[PDB]
Structure formats: structure tokens, C-alpha cells
């Protein structure tokens, strides 16, 4: 059972992580150019099975604001969890091997991140981006249901596996777009885009490995709070890695 | 818990009857349908992120008759499996626990084929849009499975159900965006039969959701789990025949 001292230490760790997210949010808000990525519709110009209009831009993602949004969401939920007011509810949740505020945050923050990665790869169709957001949110909600209905060592990973099925779909989409079957242009995917997809695919898999390790509950992973710390570190590293790779690639003032 | 021989034999034959209706429609569509196809496209960057795209390219084509036969055939197959041998014993045992895993395994494939076809009929073609629609629709079904796995009727817990509604509505928001066609240079003339498909199947999809809601509320006649089991079998039969013959009438008749 987690002790009062262990829970209080974790709340301090949440606060520190929140400060790192918040200061990066500020730096991106302040320093980023107005670089935008399109969401498009490619409408039928006739009955189904005939021809299409050219893609039209429906709206544009303000990329700096979107990066600031996923950093800011992490900061907000870390500050909420860190609060003395939430000590009773955190302790109650951690005693049931649950952190629900993590899933509420990730359902929005990780979904913003995967949409931005898709747009950076050139995925623009508004339904592609909407459905990527939804299936990524679904991945998180399956992880939430793993925590709600199972305990470590109980032999039940069904929600986890459903989360893996939902979770892999956006990444199959990215892989299709970088392979670009049927593509005409000899223009190559930029290095920095490969860097984003490869690094963030590794991090996304890392989150899945934490829930797997926690619910397997073997060796040091018998201690649920080890997973709780791992999630805080992985969110910090993943969101910083994506923020600064996008910033370096697209948001610098030489590109304004 | 054990069912009466009369109860479980009655459901066995209900499955067989539904299966025969699906199977005969599958044959009629396979035999009679033309070679009408709908594209899946890639619209690749032909420059750096935030610049220009190639014209959309067709990566592959959905053979619409075959895809309609597929969703009918999946329903037929699962109805025959559920009424057969050792699978029938598992089906009976699961019904006694207020579960039908066979239903969710089938629907995760059959309803996902259906919503992708509806998306393509509306002119959604981007291969990642269609992949992510398939994934988020599958997710909706898997949330319905987790509602049955972890909760009991009347227990007041609908969290997996609500998660299923969040995932489930995403493709339909996509369809609505495409028929409104925001940013279109000219008004988009969507055929009547396409509106028929979207409106009718939206009503049917909401009907499936209402059955699970009514079962887990468990009030009045819905306290009997098997009443919901019968409602699902009827809705699957009516929804799939409605979509099959609307697509057939709209697209599959004339020789190409
Ligand atoms: C060189 C740069 C200097 C940076 C100065 C940062 C100062 C204030 C920012 C907010 C600081 C809040 C950090 C919380 C620290 C914390 O919670 O530590 C737990 C400890 O055990 C008990 O406080
Ligand atoms: C802590 C862990 C976080 C580590 C950050 C991870 C990866 C940075 C990747 C940046 C790599 C940029 C590659 C550039 C390149 O490959 O060049 C291709 C050429 O420029 C065509 O554009
Ligand atoms: C029982 C399901 C009844 C659902 C009937 C829904 C029909 C919708 C319809 O007929 O719409 C097509 C037409 O173009 C008019 O807009
Ligand atoms: C900023 C926070 C991020 C990037 C969080 C990402 C979280 C995931 C990629 C979670 C993945 C999971 C699965 C693939 C299976 C179910 C368990 C999850 C939710 C941990
Ligand atoms: C041929 C089979 C079909 C069309 C089945 C469709 C099923 C659904 C639309 C199910 C929807 C559900 C929700 C929206 C919430 C959770 C419960 C479900 C799975 C019944
Ligand atoms: C509520 C959330 C989203 C609901 C989506 C609805 C799905 C489709 C059904 C109705 C579609 C018919 C709308 C006609 C609009 C035509 C137009 O104004 O151009
Ligand atoms: C069972 C319920 C099925 C109801 C489905 C039928 C809808 C058909 C209406 C669409 C006809 C197209 C209208 C047009 O061509 O303008
Ligand atoms: C041991 C605690 C370290 C606290 C760091 C606080 C954040 C610093 C911001 C720069
Ligand atoms: C770790 C928090 C410090 C703020 C982010 C660093 C700013 C990078 C600017 C380039
Ligand atoms: C749940 C949110 C998904 C719907 C967002 C799509 C809104 C698009 C409408 C914008 C129209 C602007 C015209 C160009
Ligand atoms: C030019 C457009 C500027 C308006 C800002 C729009 C911000 C982007 C938010 C749109 C969200 C809805 C789109 C659905 C896809 C992902 C959820
Ligand atoms: C207990 C920890 C509470 C810290 C909350 C910090 C909020 C910072 C808000 C900044 C707004 C721009
Ligand atoms: C019972 C309500 C709980 C809501 C959970 C919060 C998660 C939000 C998911 C948003 C997904 C948007 C899909 C597009
Ligand atoms: C075992 C049940 C789940 C199977 C489907 C899940 C798909 C995810 C596998 C992708 C592997 C990524 C590489 C690491
Ligand atoms: C021995 C078996 C080990 C299985 C470990 C599973 C955890 C990683 C798989 C994640 C796949 C889905 C990832 C989705 C987001 C990219
Ligand atoms: C289950 C998800 C896998 C989707 C496969 C995508 C098909 C790509 C085909 C490329 C061939 C065109 C050249
Ligand atoms: C750096 C701000 C403090 C947050 C702590 C997280 C440290 C993880 C390091 C990840 C940063 C990678 C930056 C990528 C470089 C882009 C080129
Ligand atoms: C008691 C009613 C039984 C009717 C079964 C119908 C058999 C399938 C015929 C398809 C034509
Ligand atoms: C419903 C049982 C038989 C299936 C055939 C449905 C009618 C097909 C004729 C359309 C042409
Ligand atoms: C603990 C419950 C076990 C889940 C049953 C697994 C589902 C059986 C068959 C599913 C395979 C479908 C593959 C489609 C591609
Ligand atoms: C143990 C895992 C059980 C698998 C679930 C059975 C059916 C799920 C099939 C979902 C397919 C999703 C495809 C995404 C594109
Ligand atoms: C037909 C209209 C489509 C409705 C779309 C539903 C999307 C899910 C919304 C989240 C759940 C909200 C209701 C939760 C109520 C819980 C209180 C007991
Ligand atoms: C209060 C009564 C709530 C009834 C909820 C059942 C219907 C709502 C389902 C919405 C999601 C539909 C997704 C597939 C179209
Ligand atoms: C049983 C329901 C059958 C409905 C058939 C739909 C007819 C569509 C043709 C126009
Ligand atoms: C409810 C399932 C029983 C079979 C339905 C018969 C199919 C209707 C044929 C419609 C003809 C459209 C051309």
C-alpha cells in the first residue's frame, strides 16, 4: 500500500514536471512563427464514382499555438494532481492502482500531438485528422478502462490490447504517407519529419510498455508508483522532444 | 447459470434464420452487382511541410459489390458459428453472463466495412481517413464489449458505453462535414440516394446504441437480457439489408 510520504513525494514530482511543461509552453507561445498546416476537403464534383474538385483548405492549424496547447494541458493536469485539495482523491486512486487525471489529460494532449505529426507528414484531409484524433483518444480511453476494471497480476489485459489496436492505426496512416504509394514527385520526406515520426513512435510505444509492465506487475513493477513516475518522465520527454523538433523544423523566425 | 433447453434452442434458430437472410442477400449482390469501385487516395506533399501538394492519386479501389457481400457474409458467418456445435455451448454460457462476444467480434469488422463504404459514397477517399474511420468505428464496438465484460445491468456504470458513443460519433461528424462541404468553391450536388443512406444508417447506428443503453438501464422489458440479444439480431438484419440495397440501387445496377 502506498504510504502518505510516498504519495506526497509523487505530488511534488507532478508539480516539478508541470513547471517544465509550463515554461516550454511559454517559450513556444513567445518564440514560434505563425506557421500553419491545412485541413482540407476533396469533394465529389458529381455523383459517387465520377470526379473530384481540387482539395480546398477548410481551416489551418496554428502550429505554435497547438504545440503550446499540448504542453499547457500537461502543465494544467500536473498542477491539479499536485494540489493538497486532491491528496485524498489521488491517495484513494493510487490505492486502487488508478490515475484518472492522466487519462483525461492524455486523451486531449496525445491526440493533439498525433494530429500535428500527421499534418507535418502531409496528411490534410479534415476527416483523416478528426478520425486520427478520435482513434488516438480511444487508445487512451481503453487504457483508462484497463485501470478502472483490472488490477495488476489479475491476468486480464483485454482493454490494454484494445488500446494497442486503436493506438497503432494513426501510425499505419503515417507509414502509408511516408511510403507514398502511387506518388509522382521525386521530392523526399524531410529528415526532420523522419526524426519526429521515429522518435515519437518510440515514445508512444514506451507509454504502452509502462501499462503492460504495471499490470504484469513483475519484479520492481510490482510497485505501482514506479509506473506512475515513468509516465510523468515519459510525458515530459515525449512532449519536449515533439515541441522542439516541430519548433526547429518549422517555427523558427528565419521561416516567418 | 443454465438456460432452459426451449429458450436457448429458440435463439439458436433465430440466429439461423437471420444468417440465411444475410447469406441469400450476399449471393444476390455477388451475382447481380456491377464492378462499380470507389477510390482510396493519397495527397502527398510535393514540397516542404506548409507548401504544396501533388494532385490526389488513387492508391487502390474498393470493389463495392464485393464489400457489400463482405458485410452480409460476415453476419451470415457469425450467425452460423453461434448456432454450431462447441461455439453454440460458448454462446449459451456467455448469454447466461449477459454477454455476446461473437456479436462484438462480428460488428468490429462488419459495421466498420459499412461505415467505410458510407464514407466513400459521400466522397471521402483519403486512405488515412478511411483507415482511421475503420479504427474508430472498431473502437466503438470494443467499448460496447467492455461495457458487457465489466458491468452488470442496473449497476449505474455506463462509462464504457459513453466512451463507445464518443468513438462512434466521429465518422458521422466526418460524413456531415463532407455533405456540408465547407470551403467548396461551388455548391456540391449530393445525390438523393446518398442522403437516404446517411440518414437511414445513422438512425440504425443510434438504434444499436439505444439497445445497449436500454439493457444496462435494465428497466421494464429490458431486464430480460435475451430481449436485447433479439433486438441486435433484428437491427443487424435490417441495417445491413437497408445499406446493401440502397448501395445496389444507387450504384451497382448498370453494366460498366
Ligand atoms: C537556474 C534557474 C532557477 C529556476 C527558478 C525556479 C523558481 C521558481 C519556479 C517554480 C519552482 C517550483 C518548483 C517546485 C519545487 C518542488 O515542488 O520541490 C519539492 C521539494 O521536495 C519541496 O519543495
Ligand atoms: C531525449 C530524447 C529526445 C531526442 C530527440 C530525438 C530526435 C531528434 C531527431 C532530429 C533529426 C533530424 C534529422 C535531419 C536529417 O536527417 O536530414 C535530412 C535532410 O535534411 C532532408 O531534409
Ligand atoms: C425505419 C428506418 C427509417 C429511416 C428512413 C430514412 C429515409 C431518409 C431519406 O429518405 O432521405 C433521402 C431523400 O433524399 C430525402 O432526403
Ligand atoms: C503527452 C502524453 C502522451 C504522448 C501520452 C501517450 C500515451 C500513449 C501512447 C498511451 C498508450 C497506451 C496504449 C497503446 C495501450 C493502452 C494503454 C496506453 C493508454 C498507455
Ligand atoms: C451490421 C452491424 C452493425 C451495423 C452494428 C452496429 C453497431 C453499433 C452502431 C454499435 C454502437 C454502440 C455504441 C454507439 C456505444 C457502445 C455500445 C454499442 C457498441 C452498441
Ligand atoms: C450530432 C453529431 C453529428 C451528427 C452527424 C449526422 C450524420 C448524418 C445525418 C444527417 C445528414 C443530413 C444533413 C443534410 C445537410 C445538407 C446541407 O445542409 O448541405
Ligand atoms: C428499412 C428502412 C430503409 C429505408 C431506406 C430507404 C431510403 C430510400 C430513399 C432514397 C431515394 C433517393 C431519392 C432521390 O433520388 O432523390
Ligand atoms: C529537486 C527539485 C528541483 C526543482 C526544479 C524546479 C523547476 C526549475 C525551472 C527551471
Ligand atoms: C526546461 C524549461 C526551459 C524552457 C524551454 C527552453 C527554451 C528553448 C529555446 C530554444
Ligand atoms: C468535434 C469537432 C469536429 C468538427 C470540426 C469541423 C468544423 C469545420 C467547419 C469550418 C468551416 C470554415 C469554412 C472554411
Ligand atoms: C484558417 C483557420 C483558422 C481557425 C483556427 C482553427 C483551429 C483548429 C481547430 C479545428 C478543430 C476541428 C477540426 C477537426 C480535426 C481535429 C480535431
Ligand atoms: C499546488 C500547486 C499549484 C500550482 C499552480 C500553478 C498555476 C500556474 C498558472 C500560470 C498561469 C499563466
Ligand atoms: C463520461 C464522459 C467522460 C469524457 C472523457 C474525456 C475524454 C475526451 C475525449 C475527446 C475525444 C474527441 C473525439 C474527436
Ligand atoms: C495481441 C492483441 C493485439 C494485437 C494488435 C495490436 C497491434 C500493435 C502491434 C504493433 C507493434 C509496434 C512495434 C513495437
Ligand atoms: C512479451 C509481450 C510484450 C508485449 C508488450 C506490449 C507493449 C507495446 C506494444 C504497443 C503497440 C501499440 C502501440 C500504439 C501506439 C504507437
Ligand atoms: C490493416 C491496415 C493496412 C492498410 C494497408 C494499406 C494498403 C496500401 C497498398 C499500397 C499499394 C499501392 C501501390
Ligand atoms: C528542455 C526543457 C526541459 C524539459 C525536460 C525534458 C528533457 C528531455 C529532452 C528532450 C528535448 C529534445 C529536443 C529535440 C531537439 C530538436 C532538434
Ligand atoms: C417460423 C418462421 C420461419 C421462417 C424461416 C425462413 C427461412 C429462410 C427463407 C429465405 C427465403
Ligand atoms: C431477402 C431474401 C432474398 C434476397 C434477395 C433480395 C432481393 C434482390 C433483388 C434485387 C434486384
Ligand atoms: C478474453 C477474451 C478473448 C477474446 C477473443 C478473441 C477474438 C476471437 C477472434 C478474433 C479474431 C478476428 C480477426 C479479424 C482480422
Ligand atoms: C485479444 C485481442 C482481441 C481482438 C479483438 C477482435 C476483433 C477486433 C478487430 C478490430 C480491427 C481493427 C482494424 C483497425 C484498422
Ligand atoms: C444523435 C446525437 C449524437 C450524440 C453524440 C454523443 C457523443 C458522446 C457524448 C459524451 C457523453 C455525454 C453524456 C454523459 C452523461 C453522463 C451522466 C450520467
Ligand atoms: C438519455 C438517453 C441517452 C441514450 C443514448 C443512446 C443513443 C445515443 C448514441 C450516440 C452515439 C452514436 C454513434 C453511432 C452513430
Ligand atoms: C428489411 C429491410 C429492407 C430495406 C431495403 C431498402 C431498399 C433500398 C432501395 C432504394
Ligand atoms: C430483411 C431481410 C430480408 C430480405 C430483404 C429483401 C431485399 C430487398 C430488395 C430491394 C430491391 C432493390 C433493387
Image (cartoon, coloured by chain):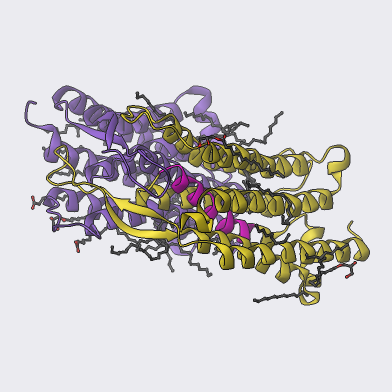
Chain colours: A yellow, B purple
Q: Position of residue A127 (x, y in %)?
A: 36, 50
B106 or B45: nearer the viewer:
B45
Q: Residue at x 76, y 52 (%)?
A: A233
Foreground: B107 or A249? A249
Q: Is residue A66 visible?
A: yes
> Among all residues in the image, which is located at the extreme left?
B254
The reply to whether residue B3 is in sight is no
Answer whether residue A11 is magenta in the image.
Answer: no
User: Which quadrant does the N terminus of chain B fall into?
Assistant: top right
| Region in magenta | A103-122
Quadrant housing residue A12: bottom right
Which of the pair B238/B171 is nearer the observer? Answer: B171
B213 with respect to B98 (left or right): left
Is residue A108 highlighted in magenta?
A: yes
The image quarter in which residue A105 lies? bottom right
- Give the percent coordinates (x, y) of residue A252: 54, 56
Residue at 15% of width from left, 54% of height from top?
Answer: B188
Amino acid at each position: 500500500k502506498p504510504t502518505v510520504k510516498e504519495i506526497k513525494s509523487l505530488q511534488n514530482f507532478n508539480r516539478i514536471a508541470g513547471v517544465f511543461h509550463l515554461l516550454q509552453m511559454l517559450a513556444v507561445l513567445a518564440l514560434a512563427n505563425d506557421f500553419a498546416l491545412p485541413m482540407t476537403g476533396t469533394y465529389l464534383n458529381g455523383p459517387p464514382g465520377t470526379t473530384f474538385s481540387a482539395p480546398v483548405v477548410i481551416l489551418e492549424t496554428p502550429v505554435g499555438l497547438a504545440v503550446a496547447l499540448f504542453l499547457g494541458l500537461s502543465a494544467l493536469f500536473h498542477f491539479i494532481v499536485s494540489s493538497g485539495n486532491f491528496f485524498k482523491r489521488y491517495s484513494a486512486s493510487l490505492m486502487k492502482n488508478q490515475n484518472i487525471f492522466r487519462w483525461v489529460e492524455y486523451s486531449l494532449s496525445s491526440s493533439v500531438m498525433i494530429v500535428l505529426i500527421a499534418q507535418i507528414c502531409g496528411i490534410a484531409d479534415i476527416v483523416a485528422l478528426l478520425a486520427i484524433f478520435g482513434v488516438n483518444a480511444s487508445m487512451i480511453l481503453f487504457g483508462w478502462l484497463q485501470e478502472k476494471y483490472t488490477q495488476p497480476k489479475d491476468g486480464d489485459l483485454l482493454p490494454f490490447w484494445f488500446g494497442c489496436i486503436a493506438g497503432i492505426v494513426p501510425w499505419i496512416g503515417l507509414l502509408i504517407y511516408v511510403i507514398a504509394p502511387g506518388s509522382t514527385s521525386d521530392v523526399a520526406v524531410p529528415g526532420f519529419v523522419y526524426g519526429i515520426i521515429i522518435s515519437l513512435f518510440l515514445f508512444f510505444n514506451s507509454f504502452a510498455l509502462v501499462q503492460y509492465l504495471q499490470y504484469k506487475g513483475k519484479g520492481k513493477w510490482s510497485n505501482y508508483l514506479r509506473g506512475e513516475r515513468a509516465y510523468i518522465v515519459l510525458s515530459l520527454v515525449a512532449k519536449s522532444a515533439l515541441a522542439w523538433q516541430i519548433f526547429s523544423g518549422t517555427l523558427i523566425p528565419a521561416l516567418e
